[PDB]
Amino acid sequence: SKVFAVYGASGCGRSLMPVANEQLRILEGDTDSQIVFIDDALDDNITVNGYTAMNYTKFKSIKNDDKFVLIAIANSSIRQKIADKLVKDGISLWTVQGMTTLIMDEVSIDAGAALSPFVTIAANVTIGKCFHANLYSYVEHDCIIGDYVTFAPRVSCNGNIHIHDHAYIGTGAVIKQGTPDKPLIIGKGAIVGMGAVVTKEVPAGAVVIGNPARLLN
Amino acid sequence: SKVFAVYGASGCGRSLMPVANEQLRILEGDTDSQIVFIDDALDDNITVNGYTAMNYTKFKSIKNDDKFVLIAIANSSIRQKIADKLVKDGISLWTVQGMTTLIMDEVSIDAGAALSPFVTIAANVTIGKCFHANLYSYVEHDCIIGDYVTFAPRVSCNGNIHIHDHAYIGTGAVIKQGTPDKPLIIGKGAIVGMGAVVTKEVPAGAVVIGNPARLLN
Amino acid sequence: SKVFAVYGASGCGRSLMPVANEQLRILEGDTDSQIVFIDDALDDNITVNGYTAMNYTKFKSIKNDDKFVLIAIANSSIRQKIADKLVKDGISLWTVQGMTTLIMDEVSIDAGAALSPFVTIAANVTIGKCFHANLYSYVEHDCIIGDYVTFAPRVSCNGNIHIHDHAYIGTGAVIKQGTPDKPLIIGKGAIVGMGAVVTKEVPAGAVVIGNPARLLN
Ligand SMILES: CC(=O)SCCNC(=O)CCNC(=O)[C@H](O)C(C)(C)COP(=O)(O)OP(=O)(O)OC[C@H]1O[C@@H](n2cnc3c(N)ncnc32)[C@H](O)[C@@H]1OP(=O)(O)O
Ligand SMILES: CC(=O)SCCNC(=O)CCNC(=O)[C@H](O)C(C)(C)COP(=O)(O)OP(=O)(O)OC[C@H]1O[C@@H](n2cnc3c(N)ncnc32)[C@H](O)[C@@H]1OP(=O)(O)O
Ligand SMILES: CC(=O)SCCNC(=O)CCNC(=O)[C@H](O)C(C)(C)COP(=O)(O)OP(=O)(O)OC[C@H]1O[C@@H](n2cnc3c(N)ncnc32)[C@H](O)[C@@H]1OP(=O)(O)O
Ligand SMILES: O=c1ccn([C@@H]2O[C@H](COP(=O)(O)OP(=O)(O)O)[C@@H](O)[C@H]2O)c(=O)[nH]1
Ligand SMILES: O=c1ccn([C@@H]2O[C@H](COP(=O)(O)OP(=O)(O)O)[C@@H](O)[C@H]2O)c(=O)[nH]1
Ligand SMILES: O=c1ccn([C@@H]2O[C@H](COP(=O)(O)OP(=O)(O)O)[C@@H](O)[C@H]2O)c(=O)[nH]1
Ligand SMILES: [Cl-]
């Protein structure tokens, strides 16, 4: 027996629950296991879009040794804190992908990724902990994505790009390919704004916007 | 018995007819009913891409009580005029979606929408009359789309956005999320240009272009 | 009997090999024929992502009358040189598309196209020799694409656009529709930069960037 959950019942979680259902019902062929929302805003259980939603205290109390959780919270510092709590409590992080999520050859993705519909992870890609690839995003050949990286929808991450931990890439941003000799680096905790056209390395902690991408003033 | 049509045999209709065929042949499992084009430019019937195409006078004359029409005319003032004519004539508006159109939980869409391939309508979205969602567009969580709204291809409509009646959103435009306390409003009859990066409310009747979006001068 | 290959085992080829496998194993229903990489950087054969990879001398030496090659080299002058060599050697150019590639009515595509996943080729489109349509690109109604044209991922090529030979369209670029009376022309060997918003004809050999697109200075 197993129990599944989506941690976060706000906009991120509500648009991931259908994906978690494709993962569980179709890709794992599991029509038996329950799936719920976990949300720490809750005191008493409620329902969200026809799913039971409970706080983490109540989820822990469920008498099952085999719990699997997708963290659907876009803020990556919260996501890391939750992931460390879940692993410490003996709960498994659970990667979810949609029926239209495309994974190519020699891809490595750490447990707990949220891979939305129409996402492509292309050849020879390595991805770290609890990656969020929102709708239509791609990661192309030979990229290395670090831990707790977050893509908004429709991110174009071209080949030979290294995105360091906790970076955020905004809606529709486009990133120029690197080369094998010089991968294009998005630094730790950088924020690439929606619609940014990134042609050069982004420093750690920088916020860049515009076409072409410049530091936000 | 039933008869189906795509109203408009120009570029919009010709790229929607295959979608109307996925809707009818696969999603409704209907291999019997005829589907035609209606176009008021026609005097004598012609064929368009192997489909009979006729004017509305001839379509009305068809002796069938059960007619279903998708309006494939991008101009929303024409679309409203046609929709009101069809309903007055006792003809049903017909929503079409592709095999790759993704609809999530608790979505409401008024009859007569044209939902193209690779479109996502995410959680808890409400959409009004004869919506056009062209190829690759998405509407994310908790959006409210009004009547006769038109998306070009690849529109990124993020969460908590309210698009009022007759707005037009151009190819590849990206719209920043609102919040539940302050939804981001695109005003009635506004035009968001192709590639616009919208970070703020757009006034009724405004035309905005650029990154970031500004009034067209 | 037949043998298949992807010519180019770098990033372009490695992200096309899974597509060539969808084309061969699923769309042609062929679980028998071998598929390999050809790459002229090789002296001795190697393996790339679990596929035999050999130089063109070794591929020619294979005793099979029935060879089919997809050229997965983005540089269109190299692609033309290879295509002419293959045809002169009596080897067939091979169009590949993914399971999620959408082709609409009355489309003509010359042999040897690389049509990636999530690509749409819409109604009444004509495409010339060895077209590259990378991930998520579309070509909308009544376009004419010439020979050895290359789209990066997520190109939005709207209706009534004529793209002349050897043009390159960069990641996420958006091109305004033409009209039947005035198709919007992208000239021979033009380069449209990633994220460019093209609202006007692009001269032959021009390099354009930005929103709106201007000559690169
Ligand atoms: C389904 C979903 O909804 S997932 C959510 C997806 N959302 C996104 O991708 C949005 C990502 N966020 C952004 O791009 C943000 O705008 C940021 C991070 C770049 C800036 O955020 P803030 O610092 O809060 O910026 P704020 O909104 O106050 O605007 C700052 C200024 O920069 C401009 N600006 C903000 N974002 C951008 C952008 N992406 N491109 C160009 N200009 C921008 C604003 O218009 C404003 O201009 P002003 O000085 O003329 O008023
Ligand atoms: C399958 C299909 O084809 S569906 C059709 C999809 N099509 C689209 O999404 C296009 C949507 N339309 C647009 O973006 C239009 O360009 C509009 C509505 C913003 C402006 O239209 P018009 O007022 O007719 O603008 P026009 O083409 O005359 O150009 C006005 C000026 O603004 C510039 N411009 C026009 N559109 C844009 C844009 N989206 N972004 C930046 N600049 C623009 C033009 O280059 C021109 O500049 P100039 O003064 O240097 O000559
Ligand atoms: C899976 C894959 O990876 S497929 C590969 C997909 N890749 C792409 O689509 C990238 C297409 N290429 C481009 O857009 C290129 O940047 C080109 C062709 C426009 C310019 O290339 P180059 O001439 O080598 O430009 P370079 O990178 O030296 O930059 C020139 C200047 O223009 C700026 N720039 C470059 N490209 C762009 C762009 N697309 N938009 C705006 N500005 C740009 C650069 O930041 C640089 O600015 P600086 O003068 O401030 O330093
Ligand atoms: O420690 C936490 C932090 C946040 N949340 C929930 O995560 C959801 C997501 O919150 P937010 O709107 O910040 O993020 P989003 O849905 O956009 O990622 C909210 O319902 C929070 O109550 C939680 O359950 N535990
Ligand atoms: O009252 C109308 C108005 C327009 N059209 C047809 O709708 C099609 C679409 O016209 P247009 O090119 O303006 O729009 P699009 O295909 O881009 O939406 C044309 O063939 C028109 O003849 C029609 O049949 N009746
Ligand atoms: O005549 C040629 C030219 C190039 N290549 C190979 O094509 C691949 C693609 O090279 P490049 O990185 O220039 O292009 P991409 O993968 O981006 O198209 C490389 O492995 C080259 O060795 C080849 O086999 N024969
Ligand atoms: Cl897309």
Image: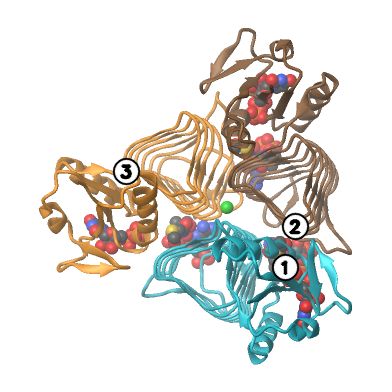
Chain colours: A orange, B cyan, C brown
| A216 shown above or below B71 | above
Label 1 sits on residue: B13
- Label 1 CB less than 8 angstroms from ligand 5: yes
Q: Is residue C150 visible?
A: yes
| C148 shown above or below A51 | above
Give, as a three-letter code, the residue at label 3.
Gly
Estimate how packed mark 3 is, as few (under 14), some (14 to 19) or many (20 or more) residues with alpha carbons within 10 Å: many
Measured in 3D between alpha carbons, the distance from the residue under mark 3 to the one under mark 2, in whole angstroms, is: 41 Å
Give, as a three-letter code, the residue at label 1.
Gly
Label 3 sits on residue: A112
Per the rendering, the mark at residue C167 is: none
| A202 shown above or below B64 | above
Label 2 sits on residue: C123
- Which residue appears at 71% of the width and 54% of the height? C104
Q: Position of residue C184 (x, y in %)?
A: 82, 57
- Which residue appears at 46% of the width and 64% of the height? B140
The answer to whether marks 2 and 1 sit on the same chain is no
Q: Taking B128 as reference, is A61 left or right?
A: left
The answer to whether marks 3 and 2 sit on the same chain is no
**Which structural element holds mark 2?**
loop
